Image (tube, coloured by chain):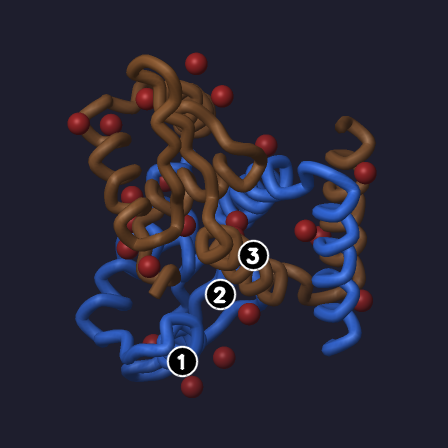
Chain colours: A brown, B blue
Amino acid sequence: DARDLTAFQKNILTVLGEEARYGLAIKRELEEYYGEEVNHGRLYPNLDDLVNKGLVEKSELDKRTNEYALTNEGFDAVVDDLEWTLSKFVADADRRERVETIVADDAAAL
Amino acid sequence: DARDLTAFQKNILTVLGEEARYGLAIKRELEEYYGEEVNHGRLYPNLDDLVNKGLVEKSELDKRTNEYALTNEGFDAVVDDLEWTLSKFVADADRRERVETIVADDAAAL
Ligand SMILES: [Br-]
Ligand SMILES: [Br-]
Ligand SMILES: [Br-]
Ligand SMILES: [Br-]
Ligand SMILES: [Br-]
Ligand SMILES: [Br-]
Ligand SMILES: [Br-]
Ligand SMILES: [Br-]
Ligand SMILES: [Br-]
Ligand SMILES: [Br-]
Ligand SMILES: [Br-]
Ligand SMILES: [Br-]
Ligand SMILES: [Br-]
Ligand SMILES: [Br-]
Ligand SMILES: [Br-]
Ligand SMILES: [Br-]
Ligand SMILES: [Br-]
Ligand SMILES: [Br-]
Ligand SMILES: [Br-]
Ligand SMILES: [Br-]
Ligand SMILES: [Br-]
Ligand SMILES: [Br-]
């Protein structure tokens, strides 16, 4: 099940939920999130795991540059965890208003 | 800085983001999420870690009965990951409408 993934693996799926990204690009996003370096020896072995699980698709582009993207299963895993997270956070009216402001501010910033 | 927590520890925080809960109640909420049994030996050592990290506060109500609640830092860690998750999910109008609908159905269930 996708609910048993590690936090690092779930964060990869989150990064790819925004848009498909080259391996090097995923590293940058994760490094910005964690605020610390992400070693090559950790990212790509986990990317391969997500590909084997059917959650991520690997597209080998021209020359040694790979683009990773969420599969339909991967996207469902991202939505599933978001729905559960929101089911626990939206516990009253103030919580709802907080999430709606976040969503609205993010969308306007697009 | 709680972005390095394990997925299991983060799920404990998410459970307590809804409301303070007894230890046994946390176990139930996690088992409903994972769809599998959560061992006593896995939950409580992680609760003790979250308490040592200052993210959860433990109140001993009775013998072998304790209630756990988020600290301010714990709640900040929950909102932090939700904000990052939403900043990546809300990538277009369709993504905004979906999250708006998720939040609306959660509020309706209250
Ligand atoms: Br899986
Ligand atoms: Br992890
Ligand atoms: Br997580
Ligand atoms: Br990219
Ligand atoms: Br690459
Ligand atoms: Br790049
Ligand atoms: Br690392
Ligand atoms: Br490697
Ligand atoms: Br989530
Ligand atoms: Br759910
Ligand atoms: Br409400
Ligand atoms: Br709030
Ligand atoms: Br921490
Ligand atoms: Br983990
Ligand atoms: Br874990
Ligand atoms: Br409870
Ligand atoms: Br307890
Ligand atoms: Br209980
Ligand atoms: Br989250
Ligand atoms: Br953010
Ligand atoms: Br929009
Ligand atoms: Br969508």
Q: Quadrant of residue A109?
A: top right
Label 1 marks which chain's residue?
A: B
Q: Sequence-wise, which precedes: disc 1 or disc 2? A: 2
Q: Which residue is mark 3?
A: A79
- Ligand 22: does it lie within 8 Å of the C-beta at label 3? yes
Label 2 marks which chain's residue?
A: B
B29 to the left or right of B101: left
Q: Position of residue B28 (x, y in %)?
A: 40, 80
Q: Residue at x 30, y 83 (%)?
A: B63
Q: Which label sits in the foreground, 1 or 3? A: 3
The quadrant of the rendering that contains the N terminus of chain A is: bottom left
Q: Position of residue B25 (x, y in %)?
A: 43, 79
Tell me the tag on residue B15.
2
**Residues packed near mark 1 inside 10 Å, few (<14), some (14 to 19) or many (20 plus):** few
Q: Work out how far the residue at label 1 is from the one at label 3, CA to CA, in angstroms.
A: 22 Å
**Above or below A91: residue B73:** above
The quadrant of the rendering that contains the C terminus of chain A is: top right
Tell me the tag on residue B28.
1
Tag 2: residue type? Val
Could you tell me if the residues under marks 1 and 3 are in contact, i.e. CB atoms within 8 Å?
Answer: no
Q: Label 3, secondary structure: give it.
A: helix
**In the image, ligand 21 is in what quadrant?**
top right
- Ligand 18: does it lie within 8 Å of the C-beta at label 1? yes
Q: Work out how far the residue at label 3 is from the one at label 2, CA to CA, in angstroms.
A: 18 Å
**Above or below B93: residue A20:** above
Tag 3: residue type? Val
